[PDB]
Amino acid sequence: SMLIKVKTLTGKEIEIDIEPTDKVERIKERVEEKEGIPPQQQRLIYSGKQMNDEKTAADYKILGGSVLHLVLA
Amino acid sequence: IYNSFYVYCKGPCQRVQPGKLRVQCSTCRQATLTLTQGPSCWDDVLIPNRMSGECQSPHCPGTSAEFFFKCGAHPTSDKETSVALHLIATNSRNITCITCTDVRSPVLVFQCNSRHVICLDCFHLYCVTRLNDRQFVHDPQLGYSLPCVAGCPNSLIKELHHFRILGEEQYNRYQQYGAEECVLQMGGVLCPRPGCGAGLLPEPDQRKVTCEGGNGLGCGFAFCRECKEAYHEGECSARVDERAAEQARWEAATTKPCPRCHVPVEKNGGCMHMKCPQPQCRLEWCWNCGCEWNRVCMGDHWFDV
Ligand SMILES: [Zn+2]
Ligand SMILES: [Zn+2]
Ligand SMILES: [Zn+2]
Ligand SMILES: [Zn+2]
Ligand SMILES: [Zn+2]
Ligand SMILES: [Zn+2]
Ligand SMILES: [Zn+2]
Ligand SMILES: [Zn+2]
């Protein structure tokens, strides 16, 4: 119900549809389902804040079209 | 018009605009929630599950309010929302800006003890200059942010969407720098290859960093942490005006009669929904406008300061 972008520091963008009530862990699963990166190697950062897997996108007040940064561990 | 609320319209406006407060049931997400009481502060409309109500939607168990904001400058879609920028306020007291000293509106008011005020033009300048100078602060909890211009303690901006005032491209730049700073704070490193700038989290054991990742995630360059050159062998060398600040303070620069029965009513926090405690009148009115309570007053100034 909400489109967001997942962006590497390299500038590769991955468009993903999410529910604002979805947990950050569910976001990582969607990244796996289309880029094949295992969630355990994914670090999501929003506006400099490392995101909590048990928190929701709505907790960060992320709106449609906004960007989460992905870093590989 | 009195506007209590300002949003960042990412839509056609591409700027800070006066906003409209709306409320729905948090369960069915319909406009079917009759609030127990009106909101009186920012906390009431920003923190989930703080205010209660009765949902009128058939067989809905919801008793919780979900508030949202829309830009009030443009004809909105039903689904769209804009982020509320709580630091911003109409400058009704005609306070001067900390930077340009001019009287402007709206203004951003920092949450420092001095409640320093700055115009949106000067706030933009502050943000742009600080972003270039790598002077943004990385907080392990609050993210990538700035305090009050004057450097007041406990003034770091918490609602990071305030930085949208940078504009779309500069905001993206702000978010890239935030992630970059976050990586460095996590003990990681940035790939030094021009056109890459990948965020890599190696161990302090392995100082053999390979830019791992395919289909545009990594470049494959192998580098040494110290020099930021190709993997080496072993160890190889190879200003705020004082008077302007003083004047730019929100605060340092009770009851009201019923419009029908002139009997004094006391305000309930910041809520502008007033009900007269006089049985023969009991008028429902707006503290600000002095008209009968309506949906326009709700959207524009349900509560204030
Ligand atoms: Zn707008
Ligand atoms: Zn409902
Ligand atoms: Zn100014
Ligand atoms: Zn201050
Ligand atoms: Zn690289
Ligand atoms: Zn070296
Ligand atoms: Zn009355
Ligand atoms: Zn009113």
Image (cartoon, helix red, strand yellow):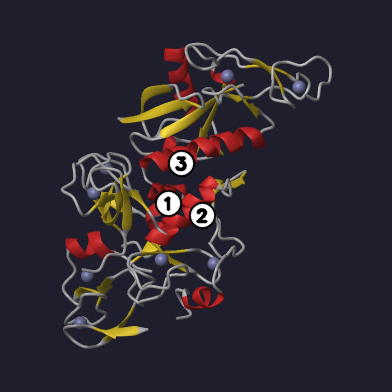
Residue identifier under label 3: A60
Tag 3, which secondary structure?
loop
Residue identifier under label 1: B162
Q: In percent of the image, x 43 and y 36: which residue is there?
A: A57
Q: Position of residue A16 (x, y in %)?
A: 37, 24
Q: CA distance from mark 1 to mark 3?
A: 13 Å
Callout 1 touching callout 3 (CB < 8 Å): no
Residue identifier under label 2: B157
Callout 1 touching callout 2 (CB < 8 Å): yes
Q: Nearer the viewer, mark 1 or mark 3?
A: 1
Q: Quadrant of residue B151?
A: bottom right
* Res. A57 in view: yes
Image quarter in which the N terminus of chain B is found = bottom left
Q: Position of residue A28 (x, y in %)?
A: 48, 23
Chain letter for mark 2 = B
Q: Share a chain, discs 1 and 2?
A: yes
Ligand 3 falls in which quarter?
bottom left
Q: Share a chain, discs 2 and 3?
A: no
Chain letter for mark 3 = A
Q: Quadrant of residue B255?
A: bottom left
Q: CA distance from mark 1 to mark 2?
A: 8 Å
Q: Position of residue B238 (x, y in %)?
A: 78, 24
Q: Earlier in the sequence, mark 1 or mark 2?
A: 2
- Name above or below for residue A44 compared with residue B299: above
Chain letter for mark 1 = B
The residue carrying pointer 1 sits among few (fewer than 14), some (14 to 19) or many (20 or more) residues within 10 Å by Cα, namely many
- Name above or below for residue B14 compared with residue B260: above
Q: Position of residue B300 (x, y in %)?
A: 24, 62
Q: Share a chain, discs 1 and 3?
A: no
Q: In percent of the image, x 45 and y 13: which residue is there?
A: A35
The residue carrying pointer 3 sits among few (fewer than 14), some (14 to 19) or many (20 or more) residues within 10 Å by Cα, namely some
